[PDB]
Length: 42
Length: 60
Length: 50
Image (cartoon, rainbow over all chains, first blue to last red; front, side):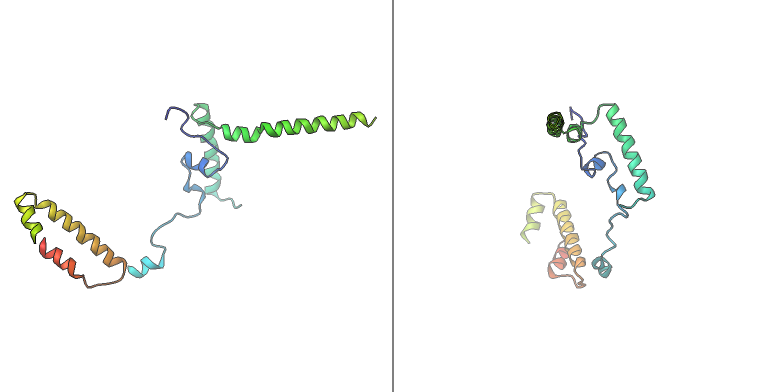
């Protein structure tokens, strides 16, 4: 809060997340309709 | 290991945002800056340089 | 049941109705997640009570 609210490290997955770009390195997002269980239920 | 338009734009935007957030002093990068400098590695390399220099000095 | 008599005498029956509707909705969700059609007895009882 008082100090720097970012604190970048050498992980690049926490670094990317802390600056907003978190899902922007994955091909496609995660959804609910992709499992056969929900399909069978529907 | 693969490069697509999304990856490229995300990488460039991340670099830009990091630089700007550093301009406003909104980021603390002591861990990265001391893992890159690595003062322990600095001392090790300095002692290695000294030993190599002594070796070259004494062979004459 | 005695719950109705109490929640009437002590006022606020609406709280009982809201809680019972929430319980009905939760039971129906659980009834959907595993494929079963006939509602159980407790669901009928909550419906009758409401």
